[PDB]
Amino acid sequence: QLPADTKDAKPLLKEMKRGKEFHVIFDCSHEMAAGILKQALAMGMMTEYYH
Amino acid sequence: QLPADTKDAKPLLKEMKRGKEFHVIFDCSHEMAAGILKQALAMGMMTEYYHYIFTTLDLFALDVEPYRYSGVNMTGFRILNTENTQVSSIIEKWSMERLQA
């Protein structure tokens, strides 16, 4: 579950990166999905490995 | 060699990514270093797999806010003795006096 306090999912994305969860399904809105993508690019989670 | 007459080195970054060249030494000015960092981030080859050594001495002037969390290891050098108090005072004085560009 994405954090509820604010649209800063950096701890969640870090935990996903540590757990080697490359294939991810996002149940959000496009406004929130854009922010999640921006924060995933900041952790290099947008590469050929991740889907 | 980075392409001439342009700063968009997307073909070069794609060639390096396809060639699986993870450790790179960049010989360019800090402006072109920032440009190539942005191109590589847009190319998706800026992760913990990649290590970049920058031979430029202005790596401290780089804006690494989008890049710190990626897990990369950007290594470089800095001859500017910023750790000194007098050097920091001179740098701040120059920055305040500049007010230009």
Image (tube, rainbow, N blue to C red):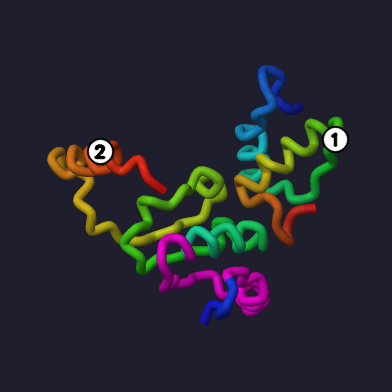
Give yes or no for residue B18 being in the magenta stretch.
Answer: yes
- Residue A39 occupies quadrant: top right
Determine the CA span between mark 1 and mark 2.
Answer: 43 Å
Residues A16 and B35: in front is B35
Which disc, if any, is residue A40? none
Q: Residue at x 22, y 38 (%)?
A: B93
Q: Which residues are magenta?
A: B7-32
Number of numbered tags placed on the structure image: 2
Number of residues whose C-alpha sits closer than 10 Å to that of mark 1, classed few (under 14), some (14–19) or many (20 or more): few
Q: Residue at x 70, y 52 (%)?
A: A46
Above or below, A41 relative to A33: below
- The answer for which chain carries disc 1 is A
Q: Chain of mark 2?
A: B
Query: Mark 1: which secondary structure?
Result: helix
Q: Residue at x 76, y 27 (%)?
A: A1
Name the residue nearer the viewer: B10 or A9: B10
Give the number of the disc on residue B92: 2
Q: Which residue is mark 1?
A: A30
Q: Are marks 1 and 2 in contact (CB under 8 Å)?
A: no
Give x and y (percent) for residue B9. 61, 72
Q: Nearer the viewer, residue A9 or B98?
A: B98
Q: Is residue B83 above or below residue B28?
A: above
Percent across and percent down for residue B42 are 66, 58
Judged from this view, the residue extending furthest toward the top is A5
* Disc 1 with disc 2 on a shared chain: no
Instruction: Residue type at mark 2: give it.
Output: Glu
- Is B78 magenta? The answer is no
Residue B55: percent from left, percent from top:
36, 68
Q: Nearer the viewer, mark 1 or mark 2?
A: 2
Neighbourhood count class around disc 2 (C-alpha, 10 Å): few under 14, some 14–19, many 20 upward: few
The residue at the point 29 percent across, 41 percent down is B95
